[PDB]
Image (cartoon, rainbow over all chains, first blue to last red; front, side, top):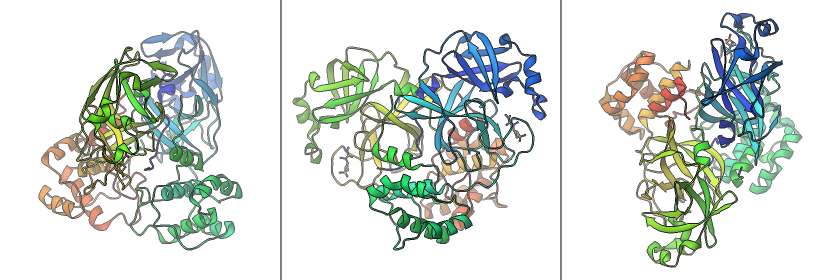
Length: 306
Length: 306
Ligand SMILES: CN(C)C(=O)N(C)[C@@H]1CCS(=O)(=O)C1
Ligand SMILES: CN(C)C(=O)N(C)[C@@H]1CCS(=O)(=O)C1
């Protein structure tokens, strides 16, 4: 027992990180097979970032202008192409450490691991959720761009995120591995609006199930509710509306604990209206929304990768 | 910017995890050079765990009774010895993935990464602190024993923890890699007392510096204090006493932010006396104590490993 914000083991992704340099800009790339994927803004000067014409900037770049380094080894670039907001650099060597992998576009509320990197070297790993406003709350400094987010399914790495930028508010935006931004964001040094950061209701309920499994039971109340009643309260507190699809996904946790999903919703409703009165749940003083129902099952049942 | 509970990249340690089986008990071992390290309680039946005589139990075990599996490969055990609460199994093959490494015994308040494993396979990675009562608050299920805690210094892995057990209160106890428990705990299924879990004051102050660096400034107050005044308040709230050694360690953070350590102590004193009034700091509703001053510098300056 115990319940922790747990990332996937990072080794499979560590073996894919390289350094990409174009002129005076260095960031991270992802080397899979004989392609290196990186943020197209590698081609930009700080001046360019104000109003970049990526097509025009790219015309001045040749294969030999992209410096790709895998630890000590230089990779030879034999082709380059722009796909949305990423560059695909074709190299003459397939990554010998390439894992089984997929490119997936995740939905808001879904979680993933970030391997934060600088100059193609890993600094750390942490768990993130795609926020309902399509931002993530990460830890990224200058040079971290091209760091990736991923999930592992036994032996297959599903890459879902590449880091591209920080909003003036200090939240993070990026793309899938086809170079399409999550949300309405663009790779330009312009003021960009994050909308309302709503709480991922289904994830809060999953974590309340985790709390019960782990003996943290004080918040269980005598009440039930309905989806419409709960949602009328969820709306007021900027919680995502809970759907029958969400109830269905929580079924296995409901079954393990013997607590009906709607009873757990009534507990959550009282926690929203009354707060925690200075108490904690799994060591948090607020309602945690970065565990999915799949995350809770996974952690509470000890599923393995290799 | 942003500030996250960040583990070390896990790849170097993933390459060291193996499965150890003795009779009907399976747990994890750590394969470094031609030695596999594991919890000595691998030799125990659930009956044995009530009052084990490890010396007597060990007499009935031969090299061929320890089944060691590295993914698909069986390792051949050519020797075994008990060191405190760990077994050292000598194998005929040096781990080809052995990193540069050290065995270190950490102090309470120090942080490390855990790679949670089952049957020699990694499930996840998270950051822990050695609590002042020498427990850790982990995420460990049946089979996780022999999972290790570690720090990385560029290319060298410092192993500091091996998981051995859960207290009836759901906190975790284990050893250094010489098999000496942290704290007064024993590898026996007996009721064992965790003492007071005090807050790591120096770590709270480091995280308050991280908050300021990351623009979360609302808690900065107009006051200062002294070490004796602050400590009189720290004691009442079960905070560890702050020493001049602690002030010294916070010097670089004090220098970066221009906030005197004692001014930050006066801010912390008001947060203890008055609480957060429903506000957050780096997305927490409580004062976080599992970042060291070294952790904050490291994360805020993007230091790299390989
Ligand atoms: C592309 N990179 C690396 C960035 O972080 N940006 C340009 C931010 C966009 C919004 S901003 O102008 O505040 C900075
Ligand atoms: C050795 N292992 C794997 C354990 O977790 N224990 C025996 C705990 C000691 C205290 S207990 O008796 O509650 C269980």
